[PDB]
Amino acid sequence: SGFRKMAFPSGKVEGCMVQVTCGTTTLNGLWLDDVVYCPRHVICTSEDMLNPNYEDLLIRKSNHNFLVQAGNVQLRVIGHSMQNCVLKLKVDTANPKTPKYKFVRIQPGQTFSVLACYNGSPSGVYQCAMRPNFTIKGSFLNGSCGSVGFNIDYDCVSFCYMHHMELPTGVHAGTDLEGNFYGPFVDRQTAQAAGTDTTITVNVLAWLYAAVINGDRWFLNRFTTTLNDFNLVAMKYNYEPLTQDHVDILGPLSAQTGIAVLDMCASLKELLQNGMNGRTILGSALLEDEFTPFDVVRQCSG
Amino acid sequence: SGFRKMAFPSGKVEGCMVQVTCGTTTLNGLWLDDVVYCPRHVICTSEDMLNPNYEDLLIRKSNHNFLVQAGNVQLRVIGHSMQNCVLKLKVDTANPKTPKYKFVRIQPGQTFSVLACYNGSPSGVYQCAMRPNFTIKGSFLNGSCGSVGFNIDYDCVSFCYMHHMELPTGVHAGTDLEGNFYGPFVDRQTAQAAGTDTTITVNVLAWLYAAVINGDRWFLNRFTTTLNDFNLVAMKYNYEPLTQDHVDILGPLSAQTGIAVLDMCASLKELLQNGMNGRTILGSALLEDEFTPFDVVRQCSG
Ligand SMILES: O=C(Cn1nnc2ccccc21)N(Cc1ccsc1)c1ccc(-c2cn[nH]c2)cc1
Ligand SMILES: O=C(Cn1nnc2ccccc21)N(Cc1ccsc1)c1ccc(-c2cn[nH]c2)cc1
């Protein structure tokens, strides 16, 4: 037993990280088959980033201006192209360490592992959720651009996130691996509104089930509620409205604990209206919304 | 910026995990050079674990009774021996993926990454601290025995922990890689007292510095304190006494933020005596003691 924020083992992704240098700037790239993916603002100077014309900036660059290093091995760039906000550098060698992989665009409320990297070298790994407002709350310093987020299904790495920017509020924004930003952000140094965030209700419920599985049961009570009544409470406390799709996803956890989803919603309602009264749940004095129902079942099944 | 509980990249350890089977039981082993390390209770049956005589149990076993599999590749066991609570299986092939490594015995209050494994296959990675009472609060299911904890220094993996047991309280106990348990525990199914735990004061202070570096400053106040006055408060709230050795370790964080350690102790004192008053620090409504001063500087330096 026990329940912790657990990242996927990062080995399959470590073998893909390279450093990408274009004149001045160095960041991280992702080497899969004979293509290296990295953020396109690698072609910018610091001044360029206020109103960069990426098309013109890229026209000034040839294959030989992109220096790509995988540890010590030097890659020979034989093609370059821009897709949305990513650069794709064709190299003449397929990465011998390429895992089975897919590119996926994840939904808000889903989680993934981030392998934070600097100069192409892995630094650490941690779990993140895509916030309802399409930001993530990560740990990224200067030089971390091009670090990627991923999930692993059996042997297949599904890459979902590439890191591009820190907003002045301190939260992080990035793209899928086709270079499309999550949310309304653009790769320009302007102030950008991250919209209203909300708490991921179905994840808080999955986490309450995780807590019951691991012995924390004090929040279980005598009450029940209805989808509509609960959604009134969710609205007041800025939680995502709960839907029948959410109820269905929580079915296995309902089945394994024998606690009906709506009875668990009644517990969450009480916690929202009265707080925790100084107690803790799975080591936290806040309601945790960064575990998906799948995250709970995976960690509670092995 | 941002600050998260960050594990080391697990790739160098993934290449070392094997499964070890001895008659009935299967668990994880660690393959380094031509030796595989695993918990000795792999030689037990379920009934054996109440009062196991490991010496006699091991005498019944020959090299060929230990089946060792590294993914699909079968290892040929050419020797076996017991060192304290670990088995060392000599195999005829050096692990080609052996990283540079050391075996270390860590001190309480130090942190490390755990690569949780089942049947020799990696499941996830997360940070743990060795509690003052030599337990760890992990996430381990049946079959996770032999999973290891480690730190990585540049290219060198320092292995510090091998997982052996879950206590009836739900916390976890294990050995160093010489097979010596941390704390008073033994590899028998008896009830065992984990002594009084305490909060790791120097880690809470390092985490408060991490918070200031990343914008959370509301707990900073007008007050100061002394080592002795603060230690009166630590005693009342079951915190480790603070020493000058701790003050010195916090020197770089003091220097980078310009907040004297004793002024930060004055903030911690106020938090302990009054609580947080519903506010949060780095996303937490509790005082966090699982980041060492080195963990803060590493994550805040790259
Ligand atoms: O946000 C960044 C880069 N970034 N990402 N995570 C960070 C954590 C700490 C500090 C900086 C961090 N920006 C701003 C921008 C606006 C639109 S996209 C990115 C950034 C700043 C400078 C460059 C640059 C490229 N060449 N020279 C400088 C790139 C991105
Ligand atoms: O605690 C364990 C094994 N273990 N470790 N983490 C666990 C998380 C969930 C469930 C079990 C877990 N024990 C008890 C014991 C007491 C002294 S050392 C270990 C355990 C139980 C059974 C065996 C066994 C060996 N052969 N057959 C059964 C081994 C350890």
Image (spheres, coloured by chain):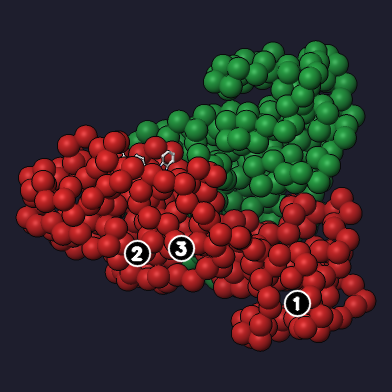
Chain colours: A red, B green
Of pointers 1 and 3, the one earlier in the residue sequence: 3
Q: Which amino acid lies under the numbered mark 3 shown in the image of this protein?
A: Gly
In this rendering, would A276 be left or right of B30?
right
Of pointers 2 and 1, the one earlier in the residue sequence: 2
Residue B244 visible in the picture: yes
x, y percent for residue A3: 66, 59
In this view, A54 is above or below A232:
above
SS label for mark 1 = helix
x, y percent for residue A78: 7, 55
Of residues B64 and A177, the one nearer the viewer is A177
Q: Are marks 1 and 3 on the same chain?
A: yes
Image point (39%, 61%), residue name: A181
- Reading the image, the residue beneath label 2 is A180
The chain carrying label 2 is: A
Tell me the number on the disc at residue A183. 3
SS label for mark 2 = loop
Where does the C terminus of chain A fall, quadrant-wise?
A: bottom right
Image point (72%, 22%), residue name: B264
- Reading the image, the residue beneath label 1 is A231
| C-alpha gap between disc 2 and disc 3 | 9 Å
Tell me the number on the disc at residue B242. none
Q: Which amino acid lies under the numbered mark 2 shown in the image of this protein?
A: Asn
| C-alpha gap between disc 2 and disc 1 | 32 Å
Of residues A275 and A10, the one nearer the viewer is A275
Q: Which amino acid lies under the numbered mark 1 shown in the image of this protein?
A: Asn
